[PDB]
View 1 (cartoon, rainbow over the protein chains, first blue to last red):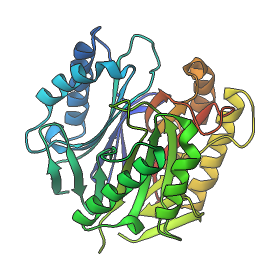
View 2: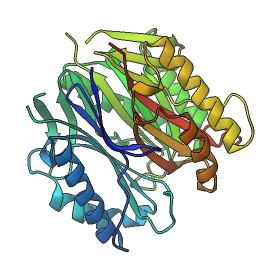
View 3: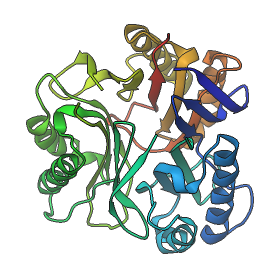
View 4: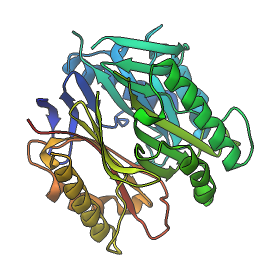
Length: 116
Length: 116
Length: 116
């Protein structure tokens, strides 16, 4: 059960891997203003970090999606639905929770697996 | 690290399994109005999905319980306590977060394991 | 995929283990009033349960931190930062959600691995 740390800071690591499993930090918007824009940005970050860890979006197991405002549900979904891999959509939960900054509309927390 | 998908939709799968591990989507109420009724319904869904993936409630590792309103803590607990397998109770966390529909008072997110 | 249960009660287990993975229940404050005091207490409980399970803070994969009030973010961080294992910081998510009692300012949910 060797642990690998990716993108380590004094506070957290962007991803942590162990025995084929990959746990991503909550990805948080770096660009965009609207729910649509920020969801695309968050998912683009997930894409990079998965690639870093030897994974991709078609190997995601689990996604918890935190929305600041549940009124943004359909907009977030439109972007999510277009990003997800057909036939390989992950387990998902979406709940409403305020994030570390007021301007952040969406945060997504991913669990994935490496390719064999 | 082969991935199995169960009850796959264009948006999510109801369950994803990898290397003996099982991740359920957040289960949301399909019947009932009060927290007690909706908790029962959610836990029955969990039973059926765990059965599908070759698991059961005695093999649940982890459960995150989201309540729309923390005022329903005790009422939810009454159904939860009666449901869990004695001596094989999982790790648990319960926090307050609004869900995708305003009528949903509870949502439960399960991690479990395949029987050998 | 044999399951080990630690600190089992009728409602939940403080920790459960399977295939070298460890899932802790949400740890909530037992002592302290301020966000700083409560965080240190929660992290001290996490230290104790990890040790029970053959693990420690340098083998934590994932941490979800729920704050009652996101106004407590920097104060929580101060304690968290001084607690983590340098170079071995885990995946992290922090999100605002009310907890089971109103005096509780912070709850932390840990996923970890056994040492070899």
